Amino acid sequence: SGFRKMAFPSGKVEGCMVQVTCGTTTLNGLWLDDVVYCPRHVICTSEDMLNPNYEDLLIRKSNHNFLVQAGNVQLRVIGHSMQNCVLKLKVDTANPKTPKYKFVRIQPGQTFSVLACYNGSPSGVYQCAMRPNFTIKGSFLNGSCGSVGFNIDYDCVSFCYMHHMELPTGVHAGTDLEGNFYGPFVDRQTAQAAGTDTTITVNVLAWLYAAVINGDRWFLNRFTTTLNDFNLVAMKYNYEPLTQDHVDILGPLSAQTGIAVLDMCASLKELLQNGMNGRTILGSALLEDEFTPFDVVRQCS
Amino acid sequence: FRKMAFPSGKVEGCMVQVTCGTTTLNGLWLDDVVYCPRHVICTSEDMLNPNYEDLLIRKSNHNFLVQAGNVQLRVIGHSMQNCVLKLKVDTANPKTPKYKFVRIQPGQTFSVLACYNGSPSGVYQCAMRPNFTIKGSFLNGSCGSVGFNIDYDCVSFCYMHHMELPTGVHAGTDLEGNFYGPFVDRQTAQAAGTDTTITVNVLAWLYAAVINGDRWFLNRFTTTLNDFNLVAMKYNYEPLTQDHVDILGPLSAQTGIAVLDMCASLKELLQNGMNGRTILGSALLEDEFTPFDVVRQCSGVT
Ligand SMILES: *C(=N)[C@H](C[C@@H]1CCNC1=O)NC(=O)[C@H](CC(C)C)NC(=O)c1ccc(-c2ccc3c(cnn3C)c2)cc1F
């Protein structure tokens, strides 16, 4: 038993982290085979970041302007290119610690682990979700750029996120490993707002099932609802609509607990309309939406 | 602020499986020794009432199967230290980090690398509760998973998982095999005492709120340590030790708020409540962030 926010073991990713420096600008890179991936704004000075013409800045750089360090060993850069907002540095040595890996672009609501790094050195690991407004509610300080998000399946690391920036509200924005931002953001030193965020309903439902599996049942009720009437209330409260695919992927939890998905939906509807009344669920005073159905099944089975 | 675990790679490189008969659990391979729970030498029926000295004298080195993945490590010695089994193996682990064995206090936090059949599955952050349980997340086969902190490049191992209690909390030992709390490695009804709130960590959390500009709860009073301890116990809060006051030193200096002034502010929060206001966005006080965790998350950690 037990239920905790849980990250993937980070060792396979730790073995890939390096430091990348251009001028006075240092951040993290990801070293896979003979290529180092990092945010392109490493090539900017402080004045460059206000309105950077990245292609001009990169054409004015040479290989020796990039200092790559794996621990105390300098890696010689022998080529460079740019793919969207990611800079790619070919080095003259293959990383012997390279895991089996893939690059994927995740969907809102999906979760991943973040290895927060500074100066190429791993600092901490934690679990994140892609928000519906395509920000992530991360924990990142100065120098964290180039830290990555990932999932692990068997022995294969699927990289899904590279960190680029923080927004005025404190949430974070970044790219996939092709350099394309999640969301309407740009790698420029300007204050940028996100769209209004919403709550990930399928994840809240998974977490309520987790609560039942671990003995928290006070929020249950006899009632059921139709899917449409649930979605009407959900949208009223800025919750994402629940699709039939969502109902289906909740099936295993429904069977494990004996609680139909639409019965649990009636419970959540009651919680939205009435609140928690000073009570807590799994120790939380708010409805948690950063566990997927898969996460709950994995931790409870 | 968010619970974050230490990077787990240095510990992942030390996880192995240990099997006796059909019982498999996890072990920790450091240099040429593997550490694991001694109840690996028990059958399910043995666990109801085990005699560990008598079970272990019937074992030889060749009864223990130690595997790093599919690779067997030959056992060349064995001994029991309290509730931990130590197996000397014929291979020194090339991935051995700099390490230490530490016994932590209630309230201290650590990362747990949850493992199954020697294979790391997940990492999460835990606090040792004042009743010497942890609110962990463990399935069957997780025994022998370890808890740790990392300081510079040194791994301090502080917990090895042994058992689940009726309330669903977890119990275990340090790496010298001494249980935290009054628990035993026997399959009987065991109860954790009623738990309490970790005062030193609530104070750390309040300092963290002040650092972020959220300081409505600061009052103009101070208190003595004795008076605060006596009041706090009436609210199911732990009393503070001198060591607690010391580890709050850095946050007190960073904010300019004496530890005892913050104690008086917390005392007011307890006697008067929150009154529908929040601290760091939350209506509950958080008690599983240590002073070190606050400094970690707010500053550059390795
Ligand atoms: C990578 N190392 C950093 C990570 C940042 C640093 C602070 N916390 C993080 O997560 N990335 C950057 O510094 C990027 C560089 C860009 C991509 C060129 N910039 C930012 O993260 C960034 C940009 C703008 C603001 C900002 C600007 C004006 C504001 C704000 C609030 N009110 N006004 C008027 C915020 C902040 C910011 F961190």
Image (cartoon, coloured by chain):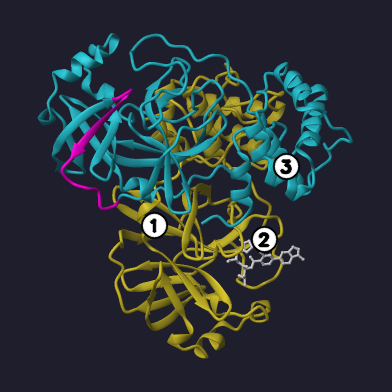
Chain colours: A yellow, B cyan
Distance Cα–Cα, label 3 vs label 1: 33 Å
Q: Do the residues indicated by labels 1 and 2 lie within the same chain of the protein?
A: yes
Q: Secondary structure at mark 3?
A: helix
**Left or right of residue B217: residue B182:** left
Q: Position of residue A218 (x, y in %)?
A: 59, 18
Whether A155 is among the magenta residues is no
Q: Position of residue B30 (x, y in %)?
A: 29, 43
Residue A138, placed above or below residue A88: above
Disc assigned to residue B207: 3
**What segment carries the magenta color?**
B81-95
Distance Cα–Cα, label 1 vs label 2: 26 Å
Q: Residues within 10 Å of mark 2 (few under 14, many from 20)?
A: some
Q: Position of residue B246 (x, y in %)?
A: 66, 38
Disc assigned to residue A13: 1
Q: Secondary structure at mark 1?
A: helix
* Ligand 1 within 8 angstroms of badge 2 C-beta: yes
Amino acid type at circle 2 is Leu
Residue depicted at 34% across the width and 17% down the height: B185
Which residue is tagged 2?
A167
Disc assigned to residue B265: none
